[PDB]
Amino acid sequence: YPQKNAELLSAQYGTNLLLLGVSVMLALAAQSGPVKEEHLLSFITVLMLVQLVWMLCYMIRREGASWIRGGLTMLALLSLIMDAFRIGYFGVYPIVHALHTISQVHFLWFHIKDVIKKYETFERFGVIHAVFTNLLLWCNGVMSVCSMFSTSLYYLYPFNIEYHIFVSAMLFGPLGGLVALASSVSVLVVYLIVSMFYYYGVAMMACMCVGSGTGLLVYTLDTELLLASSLGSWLMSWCSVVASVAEAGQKSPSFSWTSLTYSLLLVLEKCIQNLFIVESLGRKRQILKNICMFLFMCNISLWILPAFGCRPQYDNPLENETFGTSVWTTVLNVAIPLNLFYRMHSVASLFEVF
Amino acid sequence: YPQKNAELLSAQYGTNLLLLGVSVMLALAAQSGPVKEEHLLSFITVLMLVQLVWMLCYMIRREGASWIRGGLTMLALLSLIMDAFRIGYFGVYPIVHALHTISQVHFLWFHIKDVIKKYETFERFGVIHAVFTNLLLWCNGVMSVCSMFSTSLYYLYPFNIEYHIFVSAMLFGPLGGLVALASSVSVLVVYLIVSMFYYYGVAMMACMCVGSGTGLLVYTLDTELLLASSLGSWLMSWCSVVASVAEAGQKSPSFSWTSLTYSLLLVLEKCIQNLFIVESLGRKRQILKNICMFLFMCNISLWILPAFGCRPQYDNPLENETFGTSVWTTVLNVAIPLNLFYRMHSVASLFEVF
Ligand SMILES: CC(C)CCC[C@@H](C)[C@H]1CC[C@H]2[C@@H]3CC=C4C[C@@H](OC(=O)CCC(=O)O)CC[C@]4(C)[C@H]3CC[C@]12C
Ligand SMILES: CC(C)CCC[C@@H](C)[C@H]1CC[C@H]2[C@@H]3CC=C4C[C@@H](OC(=O)CCC(=O)O)CC[C@]4(C)[C@H]3CC[C@]12C
Ligand SMILES: CC(C)CCC[C@@H](C)[C@H]1CC[C@H]2[C@@H]3CC=C4C[C@@H](OC(=O)CCC(=O)O)CC[C@]4(C)[C@H]3CC[C@]12C
Ligand SMILES: CC(C)CCC[C@@H](C)[C@H]1CC[C@H]2[C@@H]3CC=C4C[C@@H](OC(=O)CCC(=O)O)CC[C@]4(C)[C@H]3CC[C@]12C
Ligand SMILES: CC(C)CCC[C@@H](C)[C@H]1CC[C@H]2[C@@H]3CC[C@@H]4C[C@@H](O)CC[C@]4(C)[C@H]3CC[C@]12C
Ligand SMILES: CC(C)CCC[C@@H](C)[C@H]1CC[C@H]2[C@@H]3CC[C@@H]4C[C@@H](O)CC[C@]4(C)[C@H]3CC[C@]12C
Ligand SMILES: CC(C)CCC[C@@H](C)[C@H]1CC[C@H]2[C@@H]3CC[C@@H]4C[C@@H](O)CC[C@]4(C)[C@H]3CC[C@]12C
Ligand SMILES: CC(C)CCC[C@@H](C)[C@H]1CC[C@H]2[C@@H]3CC[C@@H]4C[C@@H](O)CC[C@]4(C)[C@H]3CC[C@]12C
């Protein structure tokens, strides 16, 4: 049997798998009579069950990496406690999801590395199924003692979405840094006990742009992953830029050239850092070392801030009136958990450079 | 200067170019105060002007293929008369668009082939700009004597969108066939002078599936283009399948197992034909020849039918109540002009096989 056809036929299966999801999601976004949320939960439940069964059949037949695995396991633990909370609240979906999570963690830990290397068409259909089950659970995620459950679900939400992003992915000077690490926590605490976030972010992004530009002046999977994760922040930034300029057209002190500069600096920071990292992969070596140090000790600060819930973007009245509550909320729900992945990738890459 | 960075930096530019569009489109879909349609028209007008200027600078510095060029030129002629009608109705956009169309046609005809071969960073930024200007004009297209203008704009609409698809692309037995060619016109005329369309399509897709399957039993850019264009019909089909099943849950004779079979056959037909074509690229040779003949003389029939305006899908009350008028309309607006590209590609490929 020619094996190229398996790549094509499986690929067609995979895209039909995604497109069926889109159809059921579209019929749900419309909030029409015939399609209810339970139909989407049933659908994906059926896809997880199919996956589990595939893994069981595989086990029957068989009669950098450290950072990736650590991130995967910790995200899995958070996505599993997310289900412990859902199950505690009361349906069926959180149980199949918990089983799926446990399965994925185990398979990725022990087999995806080299066991799968020797393969034919069974694995080619299995992997595509897993990729489009995860990449469709991220869709469902993004779309979707009462205060105890609400608080825990809030804090765990970006980690469940990031979990799905991370699994999708796999299946398919120094003094300023050290001060910044303490400042991140200080900003978080004072926020919990708005404008400080934007001022901190602008100052931090300007310093990062200067550092990375200096490093460039002194001078394929990683580049693609950096760009793929960068798109979340780029979308969020351009939404803020469009709303800020549109309001700036009329008489309004809303923007105060602080949300526009912030958004443009975020775009510039990412566009420069991606090149610095890609290029990195006698007296000048020390400054390059200081650049690598100051940069990842800064990356961590901007990764802790959204990770611990200080995110003020959901409370912005400008881009909610401009884009709509559900649209702006969804855009933030996409950009935030992907940004939490990008920053860790950046830290690990800069560390390995150093 | 290292040239790899140009690929990365230009790529970042290109995706930011797309994301800015998305932001302005999102602020427009919301139909909020600050963003009007004129801001989107101004935006893209600015991008075309930039492109034109790029081409002028390029000309200053310089001090299968037949089917592709023919399709491009005829689509350009239809997209240009589209502007002749818009200009006749009265702003600025149709004039810049006409200039853009004339530019593209000329550049693609004489230079894109080999003149650009010798290049550095100017061309790398130029091509990405052109790709994301066209691939964003397709977005605007899809979203958007009065009866004379309405009639002409209706008939020319799929050809303007297909024009943008085609340009995006480039920048980045026998007796049954002969009868089918006459039947396509007969069906078109009787439709203009509904159920016949669905019965014809079901009969035709079942015959195509049998032919292609038989050919497979007897036994990289083209495969990717076939899949990329197939996704339009796959989305449209899964929308019909989801709405049909959801209605089938309740007591309803709407589906009548004619829209569900049609949609599933369309998916199967495409999934089998894509493999037949990819595999194709003593006594059994004659049947294979008959298969190639019967198939492209059938492909043409299903390409003439939507091309000449017999498309009844816009009048479906089921998938408009199920998905919403604007959503179902948009889905058809995507699937139809892409399907018109797929079928021509299929005919040209089968012809070359024969
Ligand atoms: C890298 C490749 C394999 C995937 C590319 C990312 C996808 C996961 C993205 C691409 C476009 C996205 C889709 C864009 C638009 C919509 C429409 C949206 O429907 C709406 O609610 C709009 C208004 C309405 O219809 O109510 C629901 C999510 C969905 C299907 C999307 C979910 C995420 C998708 C599939
Ligand atoms: C990588 C490149 C080449 C692809 C670029 C595609 C992105 C620009 C897409 C992918 C995900 C999309 C988003 C995914 C889903 C939605 C859902 C939609 O929200 C709704 O569900 C409708 C509101 C309601 O619930 O009524 C608004 C559009 C938005 C934010 C989409 C906007 C466009 C995005 C960012
Ligand atoms: C092959 C690569 C380079 C591109 C992939 C195809 C894109 C051209 C597609 C992918 C997802 C699509 C987007 C999906 C979702 C939306 C949301 C949509 O906004 C809505 O109207 C939803 C509800 C609302 O917000 O009112 C407008 C079109 C847009 C931006 C899309 C336009 C076409 C996009 C960018
Ligand atoms: C190639 C693979 C890996 C990517 C799959 C992405 C598709 C599933 C995306 C690309 C284009 C998207 C469509 C582009 C734009 C819209 C606009 C949106 O319509 C609106 O503008 C909102 C209605 C209003 O105007 O109020 C509804 C979703 C829809 C049909 C999107 C549904 C999801 C689609 C088909
Ligand atoms: C990885 C895991 C083993 C340890 C850390 C992950 C955290 C996200 C988890 C671990 C246990 C969780 C806590 C237990 C229950 C709590 C209810 C209420 O009072 C506010 C949130 C509340 C205090 C939770 C916040 C998030 C926590 C702290
Ligand atoms: C690798 C990475 C994915 C791990 C992330 C772990 C964090 C999400 C965990 C670690 C410890 C947790 C905190 C401890 C208890 C806290 C008190 C109460 O107000 C609820 C939030 C509260 C402040 C928690 C927020 C989430 C934290 C910060
Ligand atoms: C390529 C081009 C040179 C020739 C064919 C392309 C067609 C899509 C174009 C050519 C001229 C166009 C016609 C001229 C004006 C007409 C107004 C009204 O009575 C109904 C539509 C109306 C009759 C148009 C239909 C579409 C036509 C027929
Ligand atoms: C290569 C490909 C992109 C070329 C497509 C050309 C067609 C769109 C053109 C060719 C001739 C045109 C027809 C001639 C006049 C017609 C009478 C009136 O009722 C308006 C529609 C009317 C029936 C036209 C529909 C569009 C046609 C069929």
Image (cartoon, coloured by chain):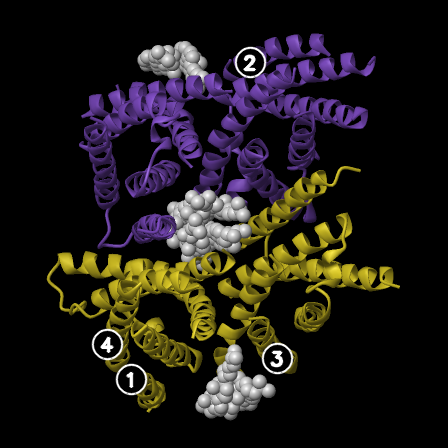
Chain colours: A purple, B yellow
Expressed as whole percent of the image width and height from the top left, the position of residue B290 reads 33, 78
**Residue A190 - label:** 2
The answer to whether residue B11 is above or below residue B307 is above
Specify whether B272 is left or right of A193: left
**Which of A191/A267 is in front?**
A267
Q: Secondary structure at mark 2?
A: helix
The disc numbered 3 marks a residue on which chain?
Answer: B
**Residue B176 - label:** 1
The disc numbered 2 marks a residue on which chain?
Answer: A
Task: Specify the quadrant of the image occupied by residue B239.
Answer: bottom left
Of all residues, the one furthest to the left in this rendering is B251
- Say which label, 4 or 1, has the lower sequence index: 1
Expressed as whole percent of the image width and height from the top left, the position of residue B46 reads 71, 59
Q: Both on one chain, marks 3 and 1?
A: yes
Kindly identify the amino acid type of the residue bearing the numbered disc 4. Answer: Ala
Q: Secondary structure at mark 3?
A: helix
Q: Which residue is mark 4?
A: B203
Beta carbon of the mark 3 residue lies under 8 A of ligand 7: yes
The Cα atoms of the two marked residues, 4 and 1, are separated by: 12 Å
Q: Secondary structure at mark 1?
A: helix
Q: Residues within 10 Å of mark 3 (few under 14, many from 20)?
A: some
Kindly identify the amino acid type of the residue bearing the numbered disc 1. Answer: Gly
Question: Would residue A43 be seen by someone viewing this image from the given angle?
Answer: yes
Q: Which residue is mark 3?
A: B77
> In the rendered image, which quarter contains the C terminus of chain A?
top right
